[PDB]
Image (spheres, coloured by chain):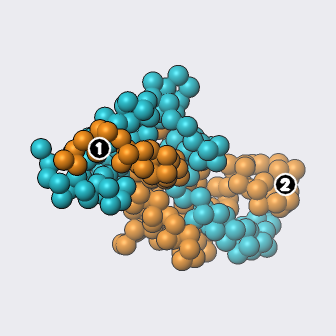
Chain colours: A orange, B cyan
Amino acid sequence: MPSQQRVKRWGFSFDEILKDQVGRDQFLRFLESEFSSENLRFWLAVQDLKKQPLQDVAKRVEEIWQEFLAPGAPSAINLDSHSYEITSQNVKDGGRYTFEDAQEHIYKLMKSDSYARFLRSNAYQDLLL
Amino acid sequence: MPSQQRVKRWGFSFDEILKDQVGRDQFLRFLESEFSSENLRFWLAVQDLKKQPLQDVAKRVEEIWQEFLAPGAPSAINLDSHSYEITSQNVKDGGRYTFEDAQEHIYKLMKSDSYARFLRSNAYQDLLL
């Protein structure tokens, strides 16, 4: 069995249960009797995602979405609409907007600092007849 | 050659140059004489990223970072510190925080709605002796 000292520590804070795998397994059996175990399994799945090699992330994200959030998901969780929409966008985006702010800065830089100069260039003006 | 009508359209707005591949190539040759072509190549690289199959994104992101932003990058661009730090975090994160808001909502849900109930459970209390 586990000691009284650690069994007591689980009742100190929720974080203490999450940190101790035996307390967490006990909590999980409780959630199963509550029919709310999908919450812990999702949380655990997302923690595991953070530890994944880069090359495995995209697949794991899709698996988490399909398991917990997609239409017809076998372990549907309930989110506030805000975090659902953000999550759905992140999953759909799939890393493709990693350089959004950077690209916007550079777009503005070219527009303000290079574009008007081009138009004044002989390179350009020589084309205009 | 290109017509006067389209050559003129390039001077209508910067977006018109970016849309027309012949105007864009002309702009690029100008940037090369300005030694600022890395700005356009970065912008173009990021546009191409948005069109990539999911399985290719992670690699392409690392290639863009290495080409334009990493220490010792062959085509160094200059960003404001803010977009640099955001970009660097996005690249490092690598999709692993796709479920950040969702996980936080579920963490709070378990803490508020399930945790205290567990502690009151016979499941738990039976362990305490």
- The dot on residue A124 is 1
Q: Is residue A20 visible?
A: yes
Q: Spatial distance from mark 1 to mark 2, Cα to Cα?
A: 74 Å
> Dot 2 corresponds to which residue?
A9
- Return the residue nearer the eye: B44 or B10: B10
Q: Compared with residue A16, is residue B41 higher up or lower down, i.e. above or below?
A: above
Q: Give left or right: position of A21 versus A59.
A: right
**Tag 2's secondary structure?**
helix
- Which chain does the residue under circle 2 lie in? A
Residue under the image location 57 percent in, 42 percent down? B79
Instruction: Locate residue B87, reporting x and y percent.
Output: 55, 44
**Tag 1's secondary structure?**
helix
Instruction: Locate residue B71, reporting x and y percent.
Output: 56, 25
Residue under the image location 60 percent in, 63 percent down? B101
Q: Compared with residue A90, is residue A120 higher up or lower down, i.e. above or below?
A: above
Q: Give left or right: position of A52 versus B101.
A: left
Instruction: Locate residue B72, reporting x and y percent.
Output: 53, 22
Q: Mark 2 is on which residue type? A: Arg
The reply to whether dot 1 and dot 2 touch (C-beta < 8 Å) is: no
Q: Mark 1 is on which residue type? A: Tyr
Q: Compared with residue A106, is residue A29 higher up or lower down, i.e. above or below?
A: below
Residue under the image location 31 percent in, 34 percent down? B29
